């Protein structure tokens, strides 16, 4: 109405309606699974295309050769936070020279995305980031929301009916740390299908793979360079 | 550059200092304070040159003023001496001034801190400083013993100040000594109008 | 010093009053006017209890030269407090 | 140009100077007032370059007026101290104003001497310029412990007589300025002992070196 | 009469019948036969009303 | 809230123009009138003060006509309040241009520069445009004697006789009727100025207290801007009696 | 962190030569305190209502008669906070004049400069103009002067004007009445009588406050003195 | 009172009403009433006393900012009356301004000047609605250096003037008239009496009374110009005396 | 409590006619829905306990945190809307760090409690920001001033505390702190006492299982805010289960 577009009107639960809308924006966006090991971090994201005479847009974006991000939601809102994450990580690398921990970086992002939620007349962003990083401790997958609230997970999946993906992840939680770079992707694939209908499984050109570590430099696999990482999947675990 | 000193009792301090504030070769005023208004509860021991002390003394008044009200009335010694470090930081070698800070904060017991003209802040036993403390360095040290007691501190401290004005070619008539407690800052005047001399050479 | 709120001080004053009239004749007459004054303050229940006290001053004072004074005090009180007081008390 | 000195009876200030205002080291004016009134009970004796003394004194003159009018309580020397302190420290040297500030403050009587740098110190008699010494020597003779207002006037006329002899730029009148809690005397003349005057003879040449040929009268 | 003007700092015309009604309320308890100065002044004191001028408001 | 109101200050309205700009013209209508007339050897300003009161002390003798510079003059038509700010901006601009230029400030140049500030507020800043139209009179060499008119709309105009303030339509025609192009000399023009002020006021009766008359006449080597004392205006008020006959005849 | 809120024009032109929101401010000064000002022609005297109607008043310096400088005094009617800023600003302005001229700010000039802020607050969004009107006195040009600066920012020139309760009625009584060629003592007596006509209730010396401007300078009359004047006249 | 009519966008803005009222200021009075704090202030010649109630939600407290007596400068002291949130922000602003005065003035500030600086700052709040005025009320007490003890009161707006005795809080007017009788009766000003007269008044208006521990009294005596809090002991000395006083 | 969703909260600079903004009242309501976070001041330190929400067995210490170190000696335990609590931690972290640069000593909590409470009130004032939606405690052990515990509400009141708790039942927990005398305790005994209260007070309607994470700034961590030592943690853990039974 106009009391739900005001960023200064709240529920009796003490929740601003504009923050609530902003979480859902993620959920209409495509499903992404982000997992960690003790040598690597893998970002598996689901693609989309406009036409058959087109290649799919990387949902894996290139920041640095040690940290990498994957988006789910609005691309334009994404790009402002992306310009912010690239600026901070590169800073860290020049000044400190430490291959930046994931854990410090997400908390500052949490501060910024919180500012429009407090501003009158300004909308929160509504993109979800699973930030994969590798520092000297080992890999971490942190998930930052359209609110401050950020998660340190072994594996996480966010998007449509994402709760179901977590269940597969929880059954193989320990395994992730032992498994290889190749397997971490295959366990990601098997989580990503749970979000989508059981009428459909993944295909080669809707999968984008983003691999992170400092035992390897950052790689984005697109639509046909996806295939080697892809093989080994189970059709709809229920 | 008159001497500054603060000698350790163990619950309050006694400072002692010599007077003359100088307008170059000529001494401009020898009827001045050596413990002017720095706050309303805090003391610093001052000498040196009028400008070197003053810039620092005021910034500490202004910061101290914020510190005292929010904490509840007494400020911290360590906080106060850091503020002086900042002024000195810019004017490193420009100002030779070094301030002798002595207090009783709510931190605990008696603390004597030496804020340098470099930018250094340290809590120690007792130091006496100035640009002329490379001159009365022996005299303080003989007086200075482990736990020099208060009654002893009155004679020792005053004497060090007396030794300074007579010998000093930057000293001058009247030692004005300052004893600081948690009650406020208290100055006393030991005369030298009347004839007191550190015994002549042959 | 203060009113102390009408209810609070009043309970205390009312209890001592009732006992004063009963026990003794002569020393009672001097204690009873002073205790009686304190109870006067309320416009609450205190009026009903003050009035009984007054009858006692009136007969005791008649014995003394205080007789002129005695009438003035009861006469004014009947005016002041018509009360919720019972008929036996009112006659 | 400005050599200033002050003395203490046991009160506040009679500030003295010999008059003359100079355009550089050439006299602009023989003897006109150079111990100054700020708004209405603070006075300043000056030394060194007179110039910095006037403008610093004028800002301070603004700020003490703010405190007097609301309080109805004496002009605050400490306020005036602080403003000057603040201006001179930033640069570490910016002009030379050697100033004898003096007013009886709301609580204690407070006398300030501001040099070229910053200070925060509190004496009770100061004599200023490079001739501080000449002014001090009259006071050290005349004034033993305790002095009176009249007596303090006699030292002050004498301090002003010494500067006139020491530097010829200061000349003529001895100005005495009484600064108190609520009595502030500015009267030019306090002692005529000399005076700069015009000639009694006249010679000037009229038309034997004069050359003219045109005239008009615009408004 | 002089006193009646003095006591309140705010009163208006409509308020004079109200303070008279208030004085009369207290007075009936006492059970009197006349109206005392005592009754008026208490009557002014309760619902005297805010000093609006000093805080903000009229001024 | 603030999002549920209208005032259409920076926002264009259905009209295609802002409310705030159009409203300012209405406020100007019921406030004291200012006219500038052209003479052959000078220019003059005559104004009705915003004071309709019967007793003035004359603390400030500029309450409508303020002389900015020794080369310029202004009048105020509108609210005295917005004038106060504008008067201070004018003493600086008028003297600044002069420091550089060393030539009497052009009447046109001044107004276009000022008009730019009037429009700046209405378009942006979220401030309303000043409720004052300022009537500038001045002289520069390359146009000659001038009168320029300033608006809150940022409109300027080159005039020879115009009036703004109260009952302006009547007033400009009345100045045209008595005074054609280049007709009337400075002295006779000062009379004409009072004659229109007597007729057009917010409240009748023209007196010394209600009027202030200013002359720009070029003296011997300098262009002299004076505001006439009450005494001189009075001699013009009798002159204005004589002038009524003269227009008709 | 940052503040927005209200930054669009709050003030709309009314056809009357003034805006709506300023017109309302002039009613505010009317419900303000009675203050009277009459120019005696050998000084100016200004008198103001001391009280804020609690009738506990204990003034020794907390006055509403305030010297700005050597020969300028201010008495006001309306708002307290709005007035304090004008007093602080006035000294800075007087002194601004004092630095350049070596004389403080004439009546006319001080008015032009105070008036520009009062208008500023109107046109701008998220601010409101003062609720204060000033009776400004001064001795300049060799003549005493008295000006009125209204809460709008407009100025009306007055030899005598009244503010506060019944201000409108106050101006007409003064316009007819106003006097000149008055001795200092008489100046006080006339001023107090005019104050009796504006101000209601009791007057003693902790109810009214008087200040005078003359040749010697502006000062503020002691509470004892005011009382002697008050008694004297009918 | 009035709630005002709009002709601007007056309703949520502080700008004028036909009463002359400012909407945000009137709302600032209701902030006083939220806190529950009421203060009675008395001026003497021995001392200036401010006495005010101390809020207890629970018995686990430290007294360093539970306290509504504040040191706004070492000699002159004050209380904030009203809503405690608005009070803390104002105290904070004032102290930075107070310290600024310390850099400028160089010494202990007069009570007249201290109230005047807060008043100018609060003029910034009052004119804005960008930032709402702070709906606390400050009574400054302290000994002005030559004049004597002074009690001045500033409103949320910032209106200040001198008074024989002043009050602030939930209701100014009712507290003042009670205090006015105490003022008429003008007692011999010495330490015990000025504190005691202040204490009796605050207790009569509430008709709840209190123990000494439940109130906080802050005095500025001619004895020590320092601003001093009596504490539990010293207040108690007055209370026991007061009981014996009629 | 007063607030209506229409009127007098349609800008964050609108003052309510009751004297307390609707927005601040809304900010307190969110604290009231959240889980209980407790912090009790001891004679030899402060012991924190905040329950860390676990929705998956995938989560590590980083997920759903409520213990921050504003300084590295000063702790912050928050309750209510996590999004605003973490942002105020970041500005606060900066504010502490600048203080340490200048001042150079373990900061006295009494100064922090005034500056932060005023900052929390500032956001109620201003249009570009809205009030903070948590109530938080600041807790430290220092030698400059000892053990200090303060709590700031989203109103922007600072009050001093011996022992406070904020949760779903703020009053029941505070009576329970009252019963026990921390005067008798040293920092070691306090860790046991915080641990039980968190389990009982909290009502599951949104949890599913929580992990208690506690932090020391005390004797065995030397005036810097570290997570609880292992011995202390185990002493604390047993008593909490025992108190249920």
Image (tube, coloured by chain):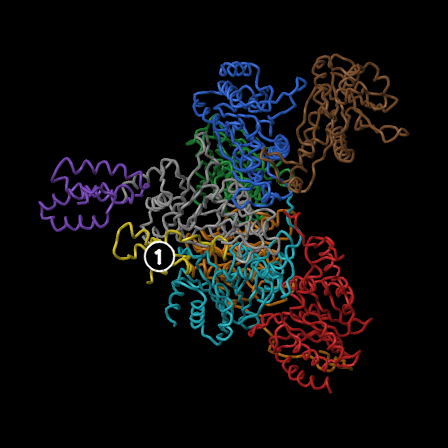
Chain colours: A brown, B green, C purple, D orange, E yellow, F red, G cyan, I blue
At a point 70% along the width and 29% down the height, the residue shown is A145
Residue at 32% in and 46% down = H193
Asked where in the image residue I224 lies, by quadrant, the reply is: top right
Q: Position of residue E43 (x, y in %)?
A: 35, 54
Q: Residue at x 46, y 50 (%)?
A: H153
- Of A202 and G61, which appears nearest the observer? A202
The correct choice, above or below, for F26 with respect to H107 in the image is: below
Q: Is residue B182 above or below residue H193?
A: above
Q: Residues within 10 Å of mark 1 (few under 14, many from 20)?
A: some
Which one is nearer the viewer's eye here, I167 or A162? A162
Residue B200: x, y in percent? Answer: 49, 38
Is residue D100 shown to the viewer in this render?
no
Q: Secondary structure at mark 1?
A: helix
Mark count: 1
- Residue G61 to residue H51: above or below: below
Which residue reaches farthest right?
A53
In the foreground, D190 or I231: I231
Where does label 1 land, which residue? E20
Which quadrant holds the N terminus of chain B? Answer: top right
Q: Name the chain letter of the residue that bears numbered label 1.
A: E
Which residue extends farthest front?
C87
Q: Is residue G222 left or right of residue A212?
A: left
Snapshot quadrant of residue G98: bottom right
Q: In the figure, is residue B120 to the left or right of I242?
A: right
Residue A3 in the image: state x and y as whole percent.
64, 41
Quarter of the rendering containing residue A143: top right
User: Between residues I122 and A198, which one lies in front from this camera angle?
Assistant: A198
The answer to whether residue D54 of the structure is visible from this angle is yes
Up the image or down, G64 lies above or below H98; here it is below
Expressed as whole percent of the image width and height from the top left, the position of residue I27 reads 57, 35
């Amino acid at each position: 109405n106009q009391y739900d577009n005001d960023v200064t009107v709240w529920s009796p639960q003490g929740r601003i309606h504009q923050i609530e809308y902003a979480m859902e924006a993620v959920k209409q966006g495509s499903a992404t699974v982000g997992l960690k090991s003790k040598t690597h971090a893998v970002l598996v994201a689901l693609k989309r295309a406009q036409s058959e005479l087109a290649a799919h847009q990387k949902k894996i974006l290139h920041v640095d050769n040690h940290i990498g991000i994957s988006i789910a939601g609005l691309t334009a809102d994404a790009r402002l936070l992306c310009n912010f994450m690239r600026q901070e990580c590169l800073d860290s690398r020049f000044v400190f020279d430490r291959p930046l921990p994931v854990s410090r970086l997400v908390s500052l992002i949490g501060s910024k995305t919180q500012i429009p939620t407090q501003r009158y007349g300004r909308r929160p962003y509504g993109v979800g980031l699973l930030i994969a990083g590798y520092d000297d401790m080992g890999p971490h997958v942190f998930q930052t929301c359209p609110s401050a609230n950020y998660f340190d997970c072994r594996a996480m999946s966010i998007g449509a009916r994402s709760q179901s993906a977590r269940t597969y992840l929880e059954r193989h939680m320990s395994e992730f740390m032992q498994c290889n770079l190749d397997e971490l992707v295959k366990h990601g694939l098997r989580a990503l299908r749970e979000t989508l209908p059981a009428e459909q499984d993944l295909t080669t050109k809707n999968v984008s793979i983003g691999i992170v570590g400092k035992d390897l430099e950052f790689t984005i696999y697109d639509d046909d360079d996806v295939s080697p990482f892809l093989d080994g999947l189970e059709e709809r675990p229920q | 550059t008159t001497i500054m000193a603060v000698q350790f009792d163990g619950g309050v301090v006694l400072g002692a200092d010599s007077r003359t504030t100088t307008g170059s070769y000529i001494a401009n005023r020898v009827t001045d304070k050596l413990t002017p208004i720095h706050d309303h509860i805090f003391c610093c021991r001052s000498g040196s040159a009028a400008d070197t002390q003053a810039v620092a003394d005021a910034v500490t008044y202004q910061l101290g003023f914020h510190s005292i009200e929010l904490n509840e009335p007494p400020l911290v010694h360590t906080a106060a001496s850091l503020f002086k470090e900042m002024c000195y930081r810019y004017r490193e070698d420009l100002m030779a001034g070094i301030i002798i800070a002595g207090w009783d904060p709510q931190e605990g017991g008696q603390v004597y801190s030496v804020p340098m003209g470099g930018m250094m802040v340290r809590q120690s036993f007792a130091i006496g400083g100035s640009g002329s403390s490379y001159i009365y360095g022996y005299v303080d040290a003989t007086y200075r013993e482990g736990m020099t007691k208060d009654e002893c501190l009155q004679f020792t401290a005053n004497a060090l100040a007396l030794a300074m004005e007579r010998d000093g070619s930057s000293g001058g008539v009247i030692r004005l000594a300052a004893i600081q407690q948690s009650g406020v800052e208290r100055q006393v005047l030991l005369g030298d109008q009347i004839p007191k001399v550190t015994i002549s050479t042959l | 010093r203060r009113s102390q709120l009408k209810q609070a001080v009043a309970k205390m004053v009312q209890q001592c009053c009732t006992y004063v009239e009963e026990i003794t004749d002569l020393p009672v007459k001097l204690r009873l006017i002073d205790t009686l004054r304190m109870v006067t303050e309320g416009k609450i229940y205190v009026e009903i209890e003050r009035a009984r006290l007054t009858k006692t001053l009136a007969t005791i004072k008649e014995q003394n030269g205080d007789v002129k004074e005695a009438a003035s005090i009861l006469q004014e009180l009947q005016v002041e407090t018509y009360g919720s007081m019972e008929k036996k008390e009112r006659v | 140009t400005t050599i200033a000195g002050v003395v203490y009876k046991d009160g506040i200030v009679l500030g003295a100077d010999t008059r003359a205002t100079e355009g550089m080291v050439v006299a602009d004016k023989n003897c006109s007032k150079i111990h100054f009134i700020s708004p209405n009970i603070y006075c300043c004796g000056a030394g060194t370059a007179a110039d910095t003394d006037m403008t610093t004194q004028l800002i301070s003159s603004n700020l003490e007026l703010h405190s007097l009018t609301t309080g109805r309580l004496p002009r605050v020397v400490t306020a005036n101290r602080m403003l000057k302190q603040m201006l001179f420290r930033y640069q570490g040297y910016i002009g030379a104003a050697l100033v004898l500030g003096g007013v009886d403050v709301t609580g204690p009587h407070l006398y300030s001497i501001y040099p070229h740098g910053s200070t925060d110190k509190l004496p009770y008699v100061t004599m200023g310029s490079g001739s501080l010494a000449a002014m001090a020597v009259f006071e050290d003779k005349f004034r033993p412990d305790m002095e009176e207002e009249e007596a303090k006037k006699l030292v002050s006329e004498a301090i002003a007589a010494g500067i006139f002899n020491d530097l010829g730029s200061g000349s003529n009148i001895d100005l005495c300025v009484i600064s108190k809690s609520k009595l502030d005397f500015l009267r030019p003349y306090s002692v005529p002992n000399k005076k700069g005057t015009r000639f009694g003879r006249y010679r000037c040449e009229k038309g034997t070196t004069a050359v003219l040929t045109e005239k008009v009268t615009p408004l | 009469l002089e006193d009646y003007v003095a006591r309140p700092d705010k009163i208006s015309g409509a308020d004079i019948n109200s303070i008279c009604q208030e004085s009369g309320m207290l007075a009936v308890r006492e059970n009197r036969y006349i109206v005392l100065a005592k009754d008026f002044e208490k009557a002014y004191k309760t619902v005297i009303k805010k000093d609006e001028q000093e805080h903000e408001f009229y001024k | 809230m603030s999002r549920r109101y209208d005032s259409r200050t920076t926002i264009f309205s259905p009209e295609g123009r802002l409310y705030q700009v159009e409203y300012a013209m209405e406020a100007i209508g019921h406030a004291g009138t200012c006219l500038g007339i052209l003479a052959n050897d000078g220019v003059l300003l005559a104004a009705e003060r915003r004071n309709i009161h019967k007793l003035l002390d004359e603390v400030f003798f500029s309450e409508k006509i303020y002389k900015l510079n020794e080369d310029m003059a202004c009048s105020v038509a509108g609210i005295t309040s917005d004038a106060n700010v504008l008067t201070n901006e004018l003493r600086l601009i008028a003297q600044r241009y002069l420091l550089q230029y060393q030539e009497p400030i052009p009447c046109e140049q001044l107004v276009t520069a000022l008009c730019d500030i009037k429009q700046a507020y209405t378009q942006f800043g979220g401030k309303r445009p000043f409720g004052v139209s300022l009537l500038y009179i001045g002289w520069d060499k390359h146009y000659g004697f001038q009168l320029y008119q300033s608006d809150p709309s940022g409109n300027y105009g080159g005039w020879k006789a115009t009036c703004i303030g109260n009952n302006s339509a009547a007033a400009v025609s009345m100045l045209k009727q008595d005074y054609k192009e280049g007709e009337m000399t400075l002295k006779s023009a000062l009379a004409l100025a009072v004659k229109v002020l007597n007729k057009t006021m917010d409240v009748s009766k023209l007196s010394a207290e209600k009027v202030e008359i200013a002359t720009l006449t070029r003296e011997n080597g300098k262009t002299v801007i004076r505001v006439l004392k009450q005494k001189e205006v009075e001699q013009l008020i009798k002159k204005h009696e004589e002038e009524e006959a003269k227009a008709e005849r | 962190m940052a503040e927005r809120g209200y930054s669009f024009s709050l003030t709309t032109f009314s056809p009357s030569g003034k805006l709506v929101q300023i017109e309302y401010a002039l009613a505010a000064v009317a419900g303000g305190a009675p203050s009277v000002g009459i120019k005696a022609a050998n000084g100016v005297v200004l008198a103001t209502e001391k009280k804020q109607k609690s009738i506990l008043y204990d003034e020794r310096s907390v006055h509403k008669v305030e010297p700005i400088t050597k020969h300028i005094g201010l008495v006001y009617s309306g708002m307290g906070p709005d007035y304090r800023v004008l007093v602080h600003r006035a000294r800075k302005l007087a002194q601004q004049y004092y630095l350049v001229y070596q004389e403080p700010i004439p009546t006319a000039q001080l008015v032009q400069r105070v008036a520009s802020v009062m208008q500023e607050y109107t046109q701008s969004g998220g601010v409101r103009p003062f609720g204060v009107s000033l009776l400004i006195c001064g001795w300049n040009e060799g003549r005493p002067y008295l000006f009125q600066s209204d809460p709008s920012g407009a100025y009306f020139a007055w030899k005598a004007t009244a503010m506060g309760k019944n201000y409108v009625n106050g101006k007409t009584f003064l316009e007819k009445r106003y006097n000149e060629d008055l001795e200092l003592e008489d100046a006080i007596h006339t001023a107090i009588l005019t104050l009796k006509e504006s101000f209601e209730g009791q007057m003693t010396e902790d109810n009214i406050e008087v200040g005078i401007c003359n040749e010697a300078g502006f000062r503020r009359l002691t509470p004892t003195e005011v009382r002697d004047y008050l008694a004297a006249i009918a | 009172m009035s709630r005002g009519s709009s002709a601007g966008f007056d309703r949520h803005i502080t700008i004028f009403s036909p009463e002359g009222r400012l909407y945000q200021v009137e709302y600032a009075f209701k902030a006083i009433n939220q806190g529950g704090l009421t203060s009675v202030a008395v001026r003497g010649k021995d001392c200036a006393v401010i006495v005010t109630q101390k809020k207890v939600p629970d018995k686990l407290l430290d007294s360093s900012t539970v306290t509504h007596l504040f040191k706004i400068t070492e000699n002159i002291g004050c209380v904030m009356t009203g809503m405690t949130a608005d009070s803390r922000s104002q105290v904070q602003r004032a102290r930075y301004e107070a310290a600024n005065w310390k850099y400028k003035y160089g010494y202990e500030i007069p009570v007249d000047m201290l109230c005047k600086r807060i008043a100018d700052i609060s003029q910034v709040y009052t004119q804005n609605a960008e930032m709402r005025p702070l709906g606390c009320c400050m009574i400054l007490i302290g000994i002005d250096e030559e004049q004597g003890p002074q009690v001045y009161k500033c409103d949320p707006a910032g209106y200040y003037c001198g008074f024989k005795a002043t009050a602030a809080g939930v209701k100014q007017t009712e507290s003042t008239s009670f205090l006015e009788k105490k003022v008429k009766k003008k007692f011999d000003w010495t330490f015990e009496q000025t504190v005691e007269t202040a204490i009796t008044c605050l207790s009569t208006v509430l008709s709840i009374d209190f123990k000494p521990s439940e109130i906080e009294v802050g005095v500025v005596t001619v004895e020590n110009p320092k601003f001093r809090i009596l504490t539990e002991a010293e207040i108690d000395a007055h209370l026991v005396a007061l009981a014996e006083r009629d | 409590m007063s607030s209506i969703g229409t009127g007098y909260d349609l800008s964050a600079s609108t003052f309510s006619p009751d004297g307390r903004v609707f927005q601040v009242e809304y900010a307190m309501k969110a604290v009231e829905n959240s889980s209980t976070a407790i912090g009790i001041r001891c004679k030899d330190g402060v012991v924190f306990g905040v329950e860390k929400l676990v929705l998956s067995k995938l989560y590590e210490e980083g997920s759903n945190k409520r213990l921050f170190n504003v300084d590295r000696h000063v702790g912050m335990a928050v309750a209510g809307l996590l999004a605003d609590a973490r942002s105020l931690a970041d500005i606060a972290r900066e504010e502490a760090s600048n203080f340490r640069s200048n001042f150079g000593y373990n900061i006295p909590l009494k100064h922090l409690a005034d500056r932060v409470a005023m900052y929390v009130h500032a956001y109620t004032l201003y249009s570009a920001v809205r009030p903070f939606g948590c109530s938080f405690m600041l807790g430290s052990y220092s030698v400059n001033d000892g053990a200090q515990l303060y709590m700031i509400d989203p109103s922007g009141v600072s009050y001093g505390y011996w022992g406070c708790a904020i949760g779903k039942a703020r009053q029941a927990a505070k009576t329970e702190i009252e019963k026990l005398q921390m005067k008798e305790m040293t920092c070691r005994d306090v860790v046991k006492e915080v641990a039980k209260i968190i389990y009982i007070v909290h009502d599951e309607v949104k949890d599913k299982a929580f992990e208690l994470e506690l932090s020391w700034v005390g004797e065995l961590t030397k005036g810097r805010h570290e997570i609880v030592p292992k011995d202390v943690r185990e002493e604390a853990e047993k008593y909490a289960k025992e108190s249920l039974k």
